[PDB]
Image (cartoon, coloured by chain):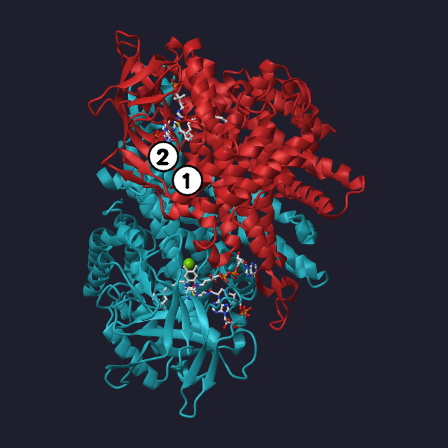
Chain colours: A cyan, B red
């Protein structure tokens, strides 16, 4: 049982952010984007949203109810037929090449538009996008490769090969540097990779593709320890003719298990055995240099952006499903007539707690969309210059700062607020007939893969703030302050934002203080760890509230100018969301600041036996 | 062993060292049950739960029940039926049952502690085993003749259902349209379709099922006050001997496909739609259906909250066991050194934060449902609290929506932390936490949604009650606060009590102001759930602080070994909860004080 047409898209909100808030249309028709105009970008969003609501979403239930089957003798996976049909619709429209470099066959576009297009695939059937990331990986291989490797990357992108990122081992998940997979140099300059990797997404994909590029982290014999000792290797499923791309003999890299998961069931998550079956796993050193963790983080950065966007896309369709249900479900009387047991029955959108729930879902779904689109505006130097006036170096540091927010805050928030979406359906929300319970199961992984929330929060504080000397964080804070410092119709929202900004500044000062104290009392560093996730989530709430308030300011201007009809309703909802978020979400940061200011190490000193 | 990890030590700590329930064991109703026998019963059912009950937890979810339209029956997986037989063969479906129906008299606090284990190990197993408890409720509401039937049903172990919901009547029970038509012989013919009925068929577990059905007699008035309650058995039977006779006209017509709790068959139930009457008997031969059914709803709400709490507890203990053995990363004090020794993940601050959050909420929630249960027996409430029967009943009624609403919501939320502790392995069906999450999502929905719990709590259990039960509990918190080692915790509790008092006053003002400005009432609705949750957090903090005060006493008296570790953990949990959970209530109070109707005035099309 399940909903075929489950996916409800929101192109209108995407276009509002892209063009009316962030002004991405400034760069369309100019420089890198000379051949792409605003009308064409809008048509592309409508087209992929239609394909996503149709053929891609059509197999969302099927992939979960009839999941992939592993044959351990052939080391291959069979995917359900309807899901492969969805994949073919993706390929036939070129949607595995969104934002691929022109020289690899893509259409040049700003990253903000690229991720808005991808949002639709991730909301309709996110595993379909994951299987379709091969050309994107080919582009990363190209950028990191030798001249000869760039030839192979060009073939792979043209032919649409699939791809995997192969880091994790049973003893090396968060601690990538603990990996033991080894690389043995051959006299001809190739390497033989030996080891067993775990949890590898898409490591086999039935007959979707002619080949799969495994990008594998391994430790050359005699290399040093930790991440710094790791190198990155191109390990193709099949050998091939490096001149023509013609597929050759099977390379020694074999799936040996497929996990049984809570959700994302149609994404084959695989134990991957390299050189264990009497056939060498030949690998080629990427770029013919030993620089593996740096190279692989080109991939990780994109995966983390995808995972946060996936969480956000899923909350959005969860909200729209809940809203559509609530508009039609009649239950109970209006609260003003509660005592009159003869009173007319009302649709549940008339109930305060349902409106509370729906506005909570709305404000977070729309605030998160704003966050990932804002982040993407720093991923092209030309867009960052045109829309923000920031140079390429600062833009890169701002993007790096925001990625743990997209991934960590996005994943955690989306899963939490889908609870409200399900609750809106009542008992029916617990049924597989409706898609919210699968959204919940499919999104639980988003706080775990591509680096757990705790790893995101440690990255955010230690690398993206401390190692950055606070430059990116100071830039964003300065933009929030400028908004606050400027019609008095958003006065209370600006005051609530000023309090939230000062709360987050207070948190940052407190955690920085603990870090400095650790120069003298090493254990003081634990308090940074204790507060790190709460700090990451606070910055996300602050950014959400600020971006919603910017959206409200645009909406006020459009209403003042004379918006009517569905436009008017849209703008009215932005004002209501920004106000609701400021009044109901932001004040909690004040208590969180005080909690962070009072952290102590009692919980660290407690005997493990006492838990 | 199995997936289910029990915590009899914490139950006994609460029952005996905190609340003093052993004070009533050996006296009056409980003349024949002593403290040692109570502890042995808890250990024994915990072992049953960890063993044969938990054994089919996975099987029930992976090989769920099948509806057969050829016979209008449901088939259950064989391994789950084996677990059910283990429950029946030890008499555990008679826990809390009246002595005249074959039970062992015991405090409700002990009853729910026993039930917690079955709810942790395989909650649908307890649901199918609720028949005797329902027979006792029928007994209590029945005529003298119906008491005879209820006695038979209890003795023979028949199953039971509570049959309220319809497609257009879930939260709004009073909108139900199922009809009851009186026959010349005084029976009734029940006609209608009910939805989402738990255990409406149960394969060959039982020889009969008692359906307790709400229906509206021809000519009755509208709403819940027009409803009556009917005894509608799956099979007719001899009212004297119990011998099973002809099939009655009450048939399951579908089984829902659910996120979790899959082995609980959740059925569309058709009454008098298959060409044979669904014969019902009016309960008590009086028309008083919603009041009668609330005897059942109260028990169901207590069960659902205890279920959620039981599940968080085994989630936590599974996560803890995993974390103690998982090696990953270096100690944070050696971050810079990429050669540092690897540590188990309990050494990482975020994992300790997560584990203490799970622990504090799991143990606070346990305290809350056991505290609640100490007001469910007049004799216990008198002995341990010094409160009379009338106030005990009102305090129990005040706390039930906390157990249900705050328990269900908190448990599901904090299981997120349990699963996170496992890392990527938590997303695997190899470990039980993802099933705990799926199975516990329903707890915020059936037996009344959280919103309905919060509206019950405020409108009925506070306003209609004139605040008497709420003032009693607040007075006990105040006394604890006013009473050295717990001075910081008492100060934080004082802030939280004042915060909850302010929320209650704001919401009351919004309600009373509705006399002159009708829309004012919407602000009560907007704040109701946050208020319910805030009270739950306050009660958690207070009860944890009371546990910490006992632990300090026991440590000063010379506790050693595993006792000492246990008491140290209680001190740590109370302190952590006071410092990291209670302060948020200050911001929630300010938010509630600032509620406005903008979100109610917004056009629906703007969402
Ligand atoms: C749009 C198209 C895109 C297409 C992409 C292609 C897709 C291919 C197919 C895959 C698609 C399927 C989707 C799968 C999604 C799930 C993916 C996974 O889980 S996969 C598994 C996911 N697994 C994880 O995500 C691992 C989670 N664990 C961590 O992230 C750890 O913190 C750790 C491993 C970094 C610690 O190791 P430790 O040694 O203490 O680390 P240190 O702090 O000392 O840094 C050392 C060096 O690392 C560097 N570098 C470090 N940080 C960053 C950064 N933020 N940022 C950048 N670079 C960073 C840096 O070089 C640094 O050197 P330096 O510049 O300082 O000199
Ligand atoms: C341990 C042994 C246990 C054995 C148990 C055996 C169980 C056998 C079956 C086993 C399977 C069942 C387990 C499965 C768990 C899920 C079961 C369900 O969902 S089932 C479906 C669960 N469905 C639900 O839970 C329905 C959710 N909906 C509600 O609760 C609504 O608020 C409503 C229907 C009450 C509103 O109707 P509205 O007419 O506006 O209400 P008003 O405010 O105007 O009150 C009218 C009358 O109702 C009365 N009464 C009311 N409240 C209480 C109370 N707290 N308290 C007491 N009584 C209460 C009261 O008589 C009052 O009259 P008065 O005293 O004032 O004169
Ligand atoms: C569905 C799925 C798909 C995946 N896809 C891929 C893939 O395609 N390629 C790939 O290489 N990997 C992939 N992974 C692996 C995934 O990235 C890891 O599961 C993740 O990094 C966590 O590692 P772990 O499971 O070993 O958990 P652990 O690292 O053992 O973490 C367990 C717990 O300890 C905490 N913890 C660990 N270290 C620290 C620390 N230093 N400080 C604080 N807390 C800490 C974690 O936050 C977590 O709560 C996938 C995993 C899943 C579940
Ligand atoms: C697994 C399962 C088993 C069940 N078992 C049984 C059983 O054995 N017997 C039985 O009789 N029923 C049973 N139920 C029915 C269950 O109690 C109802 O689903 C529940 O009461 C909610 O009703 P509903 O599904 O019609 O949701 P709705 O009442 O339609 O609620 C939808 C949404 O509106 C909100 N809402 C509704 N009215 C109000 C209001 N006045 N004010 C504010 N918000 C409001 C709800 O909170 C929810 O968010 C079961 C349900 C499930 C899911
Ligand atoms: Mg700027
Ligand atoms: Mg007392």
Q: Chain of mark 2?
A: B
Along the horizontal axis of the image, is B157 left or right of B500?
Answer: left
Number of dots carrying numbers = 2
Percent across and percent down for residue A78 are 28, 63
Question: Quadrant holding ligand 4?
Answer: top left
User: Residue A281 is drawn in which quadrant?
Assistant: bottom left
Q: Residue at (39%, 29%) from the top-left corner?
A: A352
Q: Residue at (69%, 51%) from the top-left corner?
A: A606
Q: Residue at (27%, 61%) from the top-left corner?
A: A79
Query: Which residue is labeled 2 in the image?
Result: B204
Taking the image as drawn, is residue B227 in sight? no
Q: Toward the viewer: B512 or B343?
A: B343
Along the horizontal axis of the image, is A40 left or right of A437?
Answer: left
Query: Which residue is labeled 1 in the image?
Result: B81
Q: Please, is residue A167 above or below residue A592 in the view?
A: below
Percent across and percent down for residue B324 are 60, 56
Quick one: label 2, few (<14), some, or many (20+) residues within 10 Å? few
Is there one chain holding both mark 2 and mark 1? yes
The residues tagged by marks 2 and 1 sit, at their Cα atoms, a distance apart of: 9 Å
* Secondary-structure class at tag 1: helix
CB under 8 Å between discs 2 and 1 = yes
Q: Toward the viewer: A337 or B230?
A: B230
């Amino acid at each position: 049982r399940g909903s075929m047409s489950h996916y409800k898209s929101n192109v209108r909100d995407q276009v509002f952010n892209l063009f009316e808030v962030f002004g991405v249309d400034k760069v369309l028709g100019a420089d890198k984007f000379s051949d792409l105009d605003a009308d064409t970008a809008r048509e592309m969003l409508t087209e992929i949203a239609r394909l996503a609501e149709g053929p891609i979403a059509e197999s969302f239930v099927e992939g979960d109810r009839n999941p992939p089957v592993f044959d351990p003798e052939t080391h291959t996976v069979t995917l359900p037929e309807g899901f492969k049909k969805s994949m073919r619709a993706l390929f036939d429209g070129g949607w595995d090449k969104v934002g691929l470099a022109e020289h690899l066959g893509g259409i040049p576009m700003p990253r903000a538009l690229q991720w808005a297009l991808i949002e639709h695939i991730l909301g309709a059937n996110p595993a379909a996008y994951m299987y379709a990331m091969g050309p994107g990986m080919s582009e990363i291989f190209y950028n990191n490769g030798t001249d000869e490797q760039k030839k192979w990357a060009t073939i792979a992108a043209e032919r649409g090969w699939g791809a995997t990122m192969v880091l994790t081992e049973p003893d090396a998940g968060s601690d990538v540097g603990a990996g033991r997979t080894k690389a043995v140099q051959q006299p001809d300059g190739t390497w033989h990779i030996e080891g067993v990797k775990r949890f590898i997404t898409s490591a086999d994909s039935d007959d979707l593709f002619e080949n799969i590029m495994h990008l594998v982290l391994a430790r050359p014999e005699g290399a040093g320890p930790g991440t710094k000792g790791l190198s990155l290797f191109f390990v193709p499923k099949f050998h091939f003719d490096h001149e023509t791309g013609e597929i050759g003999e099977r390379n020694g890299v074999f799936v040996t298990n497929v996990e049984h998961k809570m959700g994302l069931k149609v994404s084959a998550t695989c134990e991957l055995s390299l050189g264990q079956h009497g056939i060498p796993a030949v690998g080629w050193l990427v770029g013919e240099v030993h620089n593996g963790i740096a190279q692989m983080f080109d991939v990780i950065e994109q995966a983390r952006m995808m995972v946060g966007t996936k969480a956000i896309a899923t909350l959005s369709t969860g909200y729209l499903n809940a809203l559509e249900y609530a508009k039609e479900r009649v239950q109970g009387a209006d609260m003003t007539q509660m005592t009159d047991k003869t009173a007319p029955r009302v649709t549940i959108t008339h109930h305060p707690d349902v409106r509370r729930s729906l506005m909570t879902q709305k404000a977070y779904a729309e605030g998160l969309r704003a966050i990932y689109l804002y982040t993407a505006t720093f991923q092209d130097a030309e867009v960052a210059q045109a829309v923000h006036g920031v140079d390429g170096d600062l833009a890169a540091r701002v993007n790096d700062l925001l990625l743990p927010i997209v991934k960590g805050f996005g994943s955690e928030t989306a899963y939490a607020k889908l609870t409200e979406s399900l609750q809106t359906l009542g008992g029916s929300g617990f049924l597989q007939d409706y898609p919210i319970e699968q959204y919940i199961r499919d999104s639980k992984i988003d706080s775990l893969y591509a680096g757990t929330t705790a790893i995101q929060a440690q990255d955010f504080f230690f690398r993206k703030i401390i190692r950055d000397k606070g430059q990116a964080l100071a830039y964003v804070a300065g933009e929030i302050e400028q908004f606050i410092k400027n019609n008095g119709r958003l006065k209370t929202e600006r005051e609530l934002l000023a309090t939230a900004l000062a709360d987050v500044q207070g948190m940052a000062a407190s955690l920085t203080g603990y870090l400095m104290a650790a120069q003298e009392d090493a254990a003081s560093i634990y308090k940074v760890g204790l507060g790190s996730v709460r700090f990451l989530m606070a910055v996300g709430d602050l950014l959400s509230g600020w971006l919603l308030a910017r959206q409200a300011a645009v909406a006020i201007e459009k209403l003042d100018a004379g918006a009517t009809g569905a436009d008017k309703s849209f703008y009215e909802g932005k004002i209501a969301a920004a106000s609701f978020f400021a009044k109901n979400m932001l004040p909690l940061l004040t208590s969180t600041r005080q909690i962070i200011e009072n952290l102590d190490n009692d919980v660290m000193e407690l005997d493990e036996a006492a838990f």
